[PDB]
View 1 (cartoon, rainbow, N blue to C red):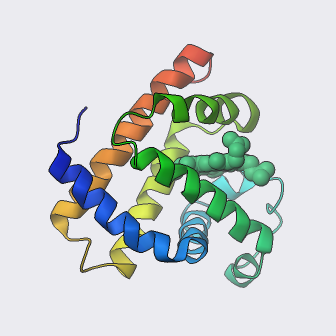
View 2 (view 1 turned 60 degrees about the vertical axis):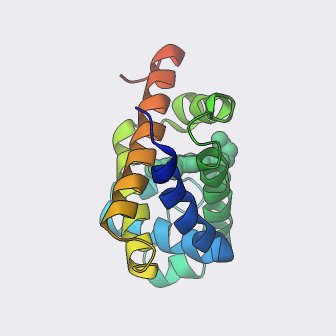
Length: 154
Ligand code: HEM
């Protein structure tokens, strides 16, 4: 696919709001993913044992990870579709070290869209949500093609 510049604008405008507090958004998003789809928590050997949302909130490791993951996602979105390089090392570790199915990336995309909608309703109207979804669909589609070249899934 290909986003127009206007769509990229809508995506990078609400992302700039996220960047005002990356660690808070990363906690909200990972907790929303683990509460909605608890099977995803099992992929993390580091926090797998967390039993409640309070324990998740208080975990520093979980918060660090959230920052690591959002930061990488932000660096990809800022590329505006020219992210080949960035995607490479990311697709490799997720396909052969962590083993993250495409379905899980869909789950976190849904968690990202849920939190942005809750926190930033003014900058996340229907058109901006359609654009963000488009950008994540692109990210998934390109990672899915990379997984296949690498020998994993699809
Ligand atoms: C927006 C999508 C995502 C981004 C941008 C992302 C980004 C990252 C980055 C940059 C790292 C550290 C370097 C590396 O290992 O490659 C990481 C590690 C990891 N990610 Fe992902 N990730 C995403 C989605 C997921 C999902 C959906 C899962 C699990 C259901 C997953 C599981 C993990 C695991 C298990 C590690 C290792 C954690 C630890 O050992 O520190 N990732 N991810």
